[PDB]
Picture (cartoon, rainbow, N blue to C red):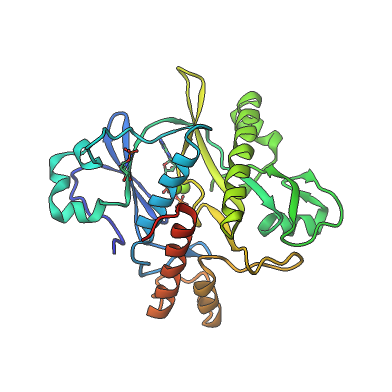
Length: 298
Ligand SMILES: Nc1ncnc2c1ncn2[C@@H]1O[C@H](COP(=O)(O)OP(=O)(O)OP(=O)(O)O)[C@@H](O)[C@H]1O
Ligand SMILES: Nc1ncnc2c1ncn2[C@@H]1O[C@H](COP(=O)(O)O)[C@@H](O)[C@H]1O
Ligand SMILES: [Mg+2]
Ligand SMILES: [Mg+2]
């Protein structure tokens, strides 16, 4: 398992997120390394879920391919017969480095990002449900009366956010990134979410909502799908089997972890080591999401 990548300065670091380490490959290219870290209640666990980052990378690769005729994406085309390692400095093929990178890394074009978190919600839950119960709105948008918890919205909706996160209205998104650009990302995001939500539902997973990020290629005026796509870290995954309108749903991937944290008053606490049984049960859910959605065997 890979918790924290250690590349000994071979590439400069651009960022470390909750789960991913981002390196600069060259002036036009980044390397996104998904680690096996996991977060709950906005804090990272001390220990890892082995191979989570491989599974999530491969799931993202599946979705990029699934959506290849719908949207351009940031992946660098790896030539036939080659691997990402052929596009990286030779030293990163040495075992001490290759073992940290293989199967969990994506080579991506640097794009100009549209600085907006493009959340699409298919189902009313989370902060959207809380706001709705209080004022009948979601990100300020008036909703029909009588929706029940976890109910499907009449149509999936664009509900933007700004990173720290702040739920904002569509009008505020247009202030931030321009009216026409906000309109284009909203329309595209809803199309992409709906297609993938329908596919996943037929496989038995409900993707209640998802967070996309987009770039813009200004030379072609094309919106580019970037960042994390339709993983349980970027989305709310629910078990289809146990879906019941009018109540909360278990987290597909994190409910075992959340239950254990809650039982021990560890929600939100730093430095927490998960017990082996929690690690194992959580890992098995990632493998099942990967196998069910991609049709591949792990
Ligand atoms: N193709 C792209 N080109 C340039 N930047 C990108 C591209 N795709 C995503 N990014 C940016 O790269 C970074 C991805 O890092 P990552 O999402 O793993 O961590 P984070 O956003 O800092 O924290 P978090 O774990 O909460 O997402 C983000 O700053 C994201 O907006
Ligand atoms: N941009 C990329 N970064 C890292 N791995 C990639 C990338 N593109 C494709 N791959 C991997 O290369 C293999 C062949 O994919 P493809 O190049 O699309 O034919 C797959 O197993 C992918 O996981
Ligand atoms: Mg991010
Ligand atoms: Mg992803």
